[PDB]
Amino acid sequence: DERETWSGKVDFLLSVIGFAVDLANVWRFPYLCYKNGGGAFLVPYGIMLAVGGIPLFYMELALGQHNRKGAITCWGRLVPLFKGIGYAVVLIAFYVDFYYNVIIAWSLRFFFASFTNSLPWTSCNNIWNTPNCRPFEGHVEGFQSAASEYFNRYILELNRSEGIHDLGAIKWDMALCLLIVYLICYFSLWKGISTSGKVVWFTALFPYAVLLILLIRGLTLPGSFLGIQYYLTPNFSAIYKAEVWVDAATQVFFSLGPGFGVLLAYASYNKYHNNVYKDALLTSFINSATSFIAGFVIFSVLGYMAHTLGVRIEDVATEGPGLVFVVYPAAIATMPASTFWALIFFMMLATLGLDSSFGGSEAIITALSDEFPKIKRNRELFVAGLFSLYFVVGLASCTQGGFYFLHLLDRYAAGYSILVAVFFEAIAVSWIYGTNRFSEDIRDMIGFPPGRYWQVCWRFVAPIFLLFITVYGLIGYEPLTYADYVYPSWANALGWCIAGSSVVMIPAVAIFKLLSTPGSLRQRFTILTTPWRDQQ
Amino acid sequence: EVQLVESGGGLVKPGGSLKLSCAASGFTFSSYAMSWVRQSPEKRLEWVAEISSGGRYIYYSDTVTGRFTISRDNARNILHLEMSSLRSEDTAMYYCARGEVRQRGFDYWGQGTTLTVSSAKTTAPSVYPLAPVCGDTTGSSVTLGCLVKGYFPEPVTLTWNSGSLSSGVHTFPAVLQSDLYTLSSSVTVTSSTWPSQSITCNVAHPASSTKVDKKIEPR
Amino acid sequence: ENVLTQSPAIMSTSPGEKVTMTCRASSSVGSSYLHWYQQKSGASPKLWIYSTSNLASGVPARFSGSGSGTSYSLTISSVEAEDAATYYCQQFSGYPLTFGSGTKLEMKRADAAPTVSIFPPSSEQLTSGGASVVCFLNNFYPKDINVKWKIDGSERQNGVLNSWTDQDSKDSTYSMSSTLTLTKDEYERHNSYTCEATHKTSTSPIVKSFNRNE
Ligand SMILES: CC(C)CCC[C@@H](C)[C@H]1CC[C@H]2[C@@H]3CC=C4C[C@@H](OC(=O)CCC(=O)O)CC[C@]4(C)[C@H]3CC[C@]12C
Ligand SMILES: CCCCCCCCCCO[C@@H]1O[C@H](CO)[C@@H](O[C@H]2O[C@H](CO)[C@@H](O)[C@H](O)[C@H]2O)[C@H](O)[C@H]1O
Ligand SMILES: CC(C)CCC[C@@H](C)[C@H]1CC[C@H]2[C@@H]3CC=C4C[C@@H](O)CC[C@]4(C)[C@H]3CC[C@]12C
Ligand SMILES: NC[C@H](O)c1ccc(O)c(O)c1
Ligand SMILES: CCCCCCCCCC
Ligand SMILES: CCCCCCCCCC
Ligand SMILES: CCCCCCCCCC
Ligand SMILES: [Cl-]
Ligand code: NA
Ligand code: NA
Ligand code: NA
Ligand code: NA
């Protein structure tokens, strides 16, 4: 019959914006600027964003709108020989939800920890502290800061684990937090986009209210301007070296999330003649804008720390979870009205993640709802069963050694898998399906064909951009380690199964059905590379 | 440099069928959607059918949907329109128009090709010369005529002295009456010019293989 | 179907004057999907204004366009003679694609009375058993003109074919041909043949006659 549609067009933009703007906008982009020549980093970042990042973002949004199905069904119809891409991409989204939500739980665990007059991560004189505790970050490995010890010894209890083999007790206060995450996700994704498209109003918008309050509070502290200098002081020497271009390339690729089945699913509920090209430019921009803003919010407070708290800038200008769960909370602890800044900061971190968890789950629910009507007829049923598997195995990550498990998933779940997956997406649409067929479809939707620029980027720039990332990725491999702990050989290999279990779907499904059509080899390719539309 | 030429097109009987062709050139034919636009003899423009660049997207007017088939040969660079079950109200000049961008319209049009759907029969014109009366012979100027009566279908071609006498000529559009066109042209020259120098009417009706010259002799 | 009506249908203007014409759609049309075509007599349309207000390649600056929703307009600031044409609007946002009913833009000029010649049946036609008298009314303005046929004294109203020319591109006049067709029998049993034209340049009609004897 008729496929449902976003109750309103802002539900779509916030769902896309919510999915694209998450914690990596805060804890990686600013760091990369600070590290790769300040403002100058914007050159290769914008070039990598213009030639590689946004072309891919646009492609998947158009594909999703035009073909009107989740990732499995969609790739089945574009190039039947490569329906495997659809499986590979849904699997990668499956693995990622196994750990991405526990990081939202951390957010909530700190939020429920900030309901107090004296934030616990301030001092070095608690039952969980060592004698080597010190009040703020330093540069000597055996002497952690008061906030590093709280996060490590009270919240995680990671000190009580000897590695991936030794997971230890289950922190039920974390398990409780994780379940609150999956409950929020349920009655948001429960009834489909009718309601999901609504809650993203809060989850995608709340982070801007909090970014605004913290931007002001941060810019008005002593030392604020010094931070912005470390953030943006141009130094074009970096641009000469490939590593900057690789960090640019890699950041733009993961910050936009193209070829993950989420943009595909979200757009598939659009109206056929919607100006998906306008939407690609608007939302992709708001994503990079949000990162630029966040840098001021972060480095304002970073300079404050270096001006009044006596810490070396390079000791607090970190990336990843340490920035938001250790360094920035430590600075909040020292300013007036600390309890307020913490409560809203962790509620921002959670809403920054929920948006994106939503999208990952939807890419699965949609893809499966569109290949298995049994599932589409029993959504509430299916989703309840999905988030229960997520939660049950998620408990592995709430154990004392749980971080060792997370770190493993994080590197492998969507590591090289996703690069290969979308590399085959770019090839499929541009070379098997054909930019002609693709441009023609777009003209039928929005009135006009994509410019020659996009056709070129989809055809040549994107795939070189993509394996430019993968080649320097491989060329810099290192066995999995965390802070003096070396993962056993068996743990490493176990991750390769996770990594390759999705990628293999591509050649497997190809082989599986290439061997299932009749006739000459040439007569079987042509059957397997004739689109579904071209056969109506 | 872009160029569009329609061909095929002529008299067809009600219920008959005919195939029009548009030869494109001066651009990459395959990057551009094309449409057929017709214009009736009452001068109304009506869009008929559109075909996407790669033939995979096709829209029809409701008035032709079912009987007409747009198609394209991106190798030979030809747009086709296959018409069948033709009715009289399909009579119009058919235009081939390039229109890839809906927001930019049809930026190139051909000269068109004319479709007449009648059950009436081709018949050749009688061309009569028109010479003045014999009274009030004031010679400042003199007006001559040529009457092309009872032909079908359109068009005819009328010139004077093989096209070299073009000033002072009024050639009136044909009018259909009882399934026959009548047409006429007037030419005006100075009395010193005529009858001293001869003036002759050149009429052509290729539909009936007619090619006749009538000299204007003075009664 | 999105029906587009245009006003006025025919409209006269003097060179230099400002001319403006309108396009009304049954249903709203996005401004990027509304275009204008110019078509000169006996030629084919040319894209003229696209996306509401942009001039197509080669369209002089005296032309402009504006509008939105269901009301658009085309405006010539200082009109020239080479602007005599019919202008069609078109919406491209919904199938079926539709064109407006058009506005014919004609040129105003000084009134001018017609030159009336009358022509008896040629001898060849009379052989074939037919007799048709022709009257030319040439180079007048404005377009409206009224011919009356008189066979002897009685006016004959039936059996006539009237054709008008398009406005001449050089002197902006109109011309008209009228043809009365009788049988040879009918023709040779009458004597006086009068074609008389009534035009705004005079209340008495211009008369041309001839007797079948002389
Ligand atoms: C870092 C934050 C704070 C600022 C945002 C920077 C980017 C959003 C800018 C930098 C370079 C820009 C790009 C530079 C040029 C292009 C090509 C341009 O392509 C065309 O117009 C030609 C194709 C056609 O005919 O449409 C479309 C916009 C785009 C992608 C731009 C989109 C916006 C970009 C990515
Ligand atoms: C939506 C409703 C559902 C609630 C979900 C919240 C679950 C989080 C785990 C709760 O466990 C408690 O968390 C407190 C905070 O971490 C601890 O207080 C400890 O830390 C506080 C400061 O953070 C102090 O006020 C207390 O004195 C001190 O006992 C307390 O010991 C601990 O058992
Ligand atoms: C200094 C910082 C905090 C400024 C924050 C700017 C905020 C207000 C910006 C960031 C993202 C923007 C939203 C992006 C998307 C849309 C969809 C559009 O159709 C309606 C406006 C709306 C909803 C914008 C509202 C304003 C907005 C939320
Ligand atoms: N912004 C992309 C981010 O890495 C991400 C989060 C959750 C997901 O399910 C996913 O596929 C990707
Ligand atoms: C990825 C498979 C997860 C299984 C969920 C439970 C299925 C319930 C069928 C209604
Ligand atoms: C920090 C970037 C996100 C994880 C990437 C894992 C593989 C990197 C290949 C270059
Ligand atoms: C629709 C095709 C399903 C392919 C069979 C399962 C893949 C084999 C992986 C080892
Ligand atoms: Cl970013
Ligand atoms: Na998010
Ligand atoms: Na991002
Ligand atoms: Na008009
Ligand atoms: Na009209």
Image: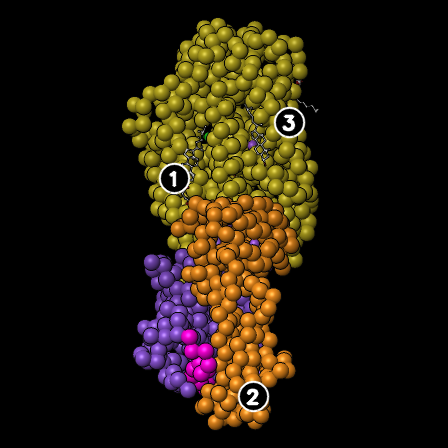
Chain colours: A yellow, B purple, C orange
Task: Report whether the residue tagged 3 is closer than 8 Å to ligand 2.
Answer: yes
Q: Is residue A142 magenta?
A: no
Which residue corresponds to mark 3?
A177
Mark 1 and mark 2 on one chain:
no
Q: Quadrant of the N terminus of chain A?
A: bottom right
Q: CA distance from mark 1 to mark 2?
A: 90 Å
Residue type, mark 2 in image: Asn
* Image mark 2: chain: C
Which of discs 3 and 1 lies nearer the camera? The answer is 1
Q: Is residue B130 magenta?
A: yes
Q: Residue at x 31, y 31 (%)?
A: A242
Which residue corresponds to mark 2?
C191
Q: Secondary structure at mark 1?
A: helix
Q: Residue at x 50, y 56 (%)?
A: C109
Q: Secondary structure at mark 2?
A: loop
Measuring from the top left, give residue B31's x and y in whole percent: 40, 57
Give above or below for C186 relative to B37: below
Foreground residue among A181 and C101: C101
Which residue corresponds to mark 1?
A51
Which span of residues is magenta-colored?
Answer: B123-138
Q: CA distance from mark 2 to mark 3?
A: 115 Å
CB atoms of marks 2 and 3 within 8 Å: no
Give above or below for A133 relative to A460: above
Mark 2 and mark 3 on one chain:
no
* Image mark 1: chain: A
Question: How many neighbours does mark 3 have within 10 angstroms: few (below 14), some (14-19), or many (20 or more)?
Answer: many
